[PDB]
Image 1 (tube, each protein chain N blue to C red):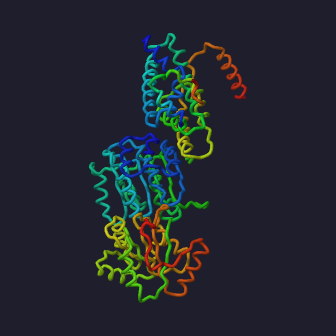
Image 2 (cartoon, rainbow over the protein chains, first blue to last red):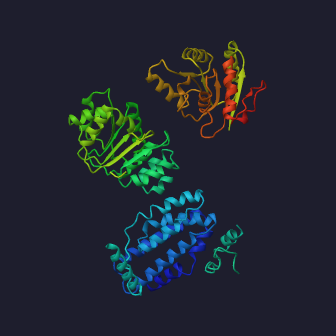
Length: 164
Length: 28
Length: 361
C-alpha cells in the first residue's frame, strides 16, 4: 500500500499527463484513457468500501483536483491535436467521474467554449452533454477542515436570504 | 509539427522532464 | 460507429453497424439523446433523413423484454409503410433475440392475427400497425395494452387530420397506461395541427431517328445503369418491348398499372437485377438510386423544374454522372433555352465524336 500510493502519486502529479496527451496519436490517447478509467474505478471502489479513511481522503481529493486541473488546462489550447486528444480521453474517462459537483461544473464550463464550427467543435458538443447528465455527485464527503466551511456557511446564508 | 516529432522521439528517454513543454518551444 | 457515442447496448450497436449506419444525421443526434430518457418527442424534419431510426433506436434502447407483454405500439397510415417499419424493426433487432416484432394491417384474417398474438413463439413486444386493425383488435380484446410504455405515431399530421384515423388512435391511446413515453413524427406539421459535378448535353434531331440513335448510344457509352424518361406510358412500354427484343435487359414503370407490379419492378431494379429502366415523370421526384451514371431524356418536359427533377436522379449526393437529352420540336428548344437562364448552366450540343468516359465517372 505504501509503495503503491507513492507510485500513483508520482504518476498523477509532476505534470506528465498534459504533454503526454499532446504527443500520442488518437488510439494511444484512447488506450491511456482506458487505463485511467480502470485505475480510478478501482481507487473509488476502495474508498467507498471505507478501507481508506485516515488520511487517504485528503490525498485522494488532491489527486482528483490535480487531474481535473490538468484536463481543464489541456482541453483549452488552439491546436487541433490537443483538442481531439482531450475529447477522446474524456470520452473514455467520464464514465466514472463522481467527484465533487464543483469539478463536473468546472469541466462543463471549460468544455463550453463553442468557438468557430469545425469537426472538433461538432465532437465537443456531445462531450459537453452526456457528462452534465450525471448531476448526482457528492461534495460533502470531501472535508470541512479549511476555512471553506465558512464559505459554505456564507453560501447557506445567501440561500436562506433567497428562500424568502 | 517539429515539436510533435521531437516529442514522439523523446518519449522513451527523458519522459519526466516534460513539464517544461507547456505549449511552447522545447525548453532545453 | 458514431452511435457508440450514444452509450447504448453492445448487441444493438452491432445491429446498427451491420446496417451501414456510421455517422448520425442532425435530427438523430438532436433527438435520440433526449428520447432515451423517456420524454415525449414531436419531430418535424425533411423527408428521407432517417426519422424512423430515431425512435427505432430509442425504443430498442428503453425496452426490457417481458414475455407476452406489449409495451411498444407504433401507428402508421398504410400497410406497405407498416411493412417497412416492421422491416426496420427487424434489421434493428438482429442481435436482440428475446424481443419480438409484429405488424398489423388490413387484408388479413383477424383470427390469424389473434392466434399469432396468443402464441408464445410469436407473442410480440413491439407492434407496428394501422390504427383501424389494431382498434379492431383492442376493442375485441384480441391484444392487451395494459402495460404499454412506448407509443409512436408516424406521419401524425394525417393521423390527426383524418377523423377515423384520429378516433382510432385515440381509442388505442386511452387503452394504454397514462404514464408512457409518447412520440409523434412527421415531415409536415402546420401550426393548425407531456412536456415535449453533373454533365449536361442535348441532341437536336427528328423523331424518326431516336430509336436507332439510342441503339448506338446505349452501345458505345460505358455505363453502370441507364434510365429512360418518356412523356407517355404507351411509348415507354413500346420502347421497353423493343429494347428487351434488342438483347438489352430493360424494365418499365409508369402509371395506368397496378401498384403491386410497380413496387415489384421498382424494388427489382433497385437491387441491380437489370441494367436498363424506363419510366415517365412518375419517378420525377423522390427516387434515390446510386448506381445510375448515364441518363437519356427521350422526351423533354414542359417546364424547367421538371427537367431538373429528372436530372436529379443522377449524381446523387454530389457524385459524378452524365446526362444527354433529345430535342425534336420547338417547345423542346424553348425549355432548353429557359433552363440555362434559371440554372446558370451551359447545355452544350452533344458532339459527334463522343466524350471522354472519365469526364463522368
